[PDB]
Image (cartoon, coloured by chain):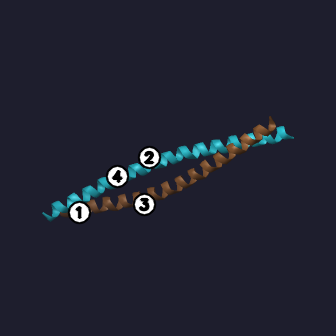
Chain colours: A brown, B cyan
Amino acid sequence: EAEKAADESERGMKVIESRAQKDEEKMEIQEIQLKEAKHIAEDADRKYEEVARKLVI
Amino acid sequence: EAEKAADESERGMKVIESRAQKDEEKMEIQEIQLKEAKHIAEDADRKYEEVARKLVI
């Protein structure tokens, strides 16, 4: 009984560690792309405002 | 001895699985935010190009 429980625990720990590392990588890449996209959005909004004012003129 | 080892492994497995699941949920939220940022970027880009073309005309 103890042998079987130990084997199953080892396998579960392996799979959980793999999933956790995958999650950490996904979180990092998501944050990076999120920040880049937010900066691009700021640039686009600023350009839109400037060109709109010039258009009214 | 085997019972003690199995119980310790069980506790470690449970805590690591819980932390992995929570970080996965937060990663999903981050992906949703990234998708919204993508949409905002595309919309602002269309705004800018349309306004520039109108100004040229």
In this view, the residue farthest toward the right is B1
At horizontal 52% and vertical 48% (from top left) the residue drawn is: B27
Q: Which mark is residue B40?
A: 4
Amino acid tagged 2: Ile
The percent coordinates of residue B43 (x first, y second) are 30, 53
Q: Which label lies toward us, 4 or 1?
A: 4
Q: Which label lies toward us, 2 or 1?
A: 2
Q: Which residue is mark 1?
A: A51
* Crowdedness near tag 4: few (<14), some (14–19) or many (≥20) residues, C-alpha within 10 Å: some
Distance between the alpha carbons at the discs numbered 2 and 3: 15 Å
Distance between the alpha carbons at the discs numbered 3 and 4: 13 Å
Image vertical order of residue B22 relative to residue A44, above or below: above
Q: Which residue is mark 2?
A: B32
* Crowdedness near tag 3: few (<14), some (14–19) or many (≥20) residues, C-alpha within 10 Å: few
At horizontal 44% and vertical 55% (from top left) the residue drawn is: A34
The tag earlier along the polypeptide, 2 or 4, is 2
The quadrant of the rendering that contains the C terminus of chain A is bottom left
The residue nearer to you, when weighing A22 against B29, is A22
Proximity of marks 3 and 4: CB atoms separated by less than 8 Å: no
Q: Which residue is mark 3?
A: A36
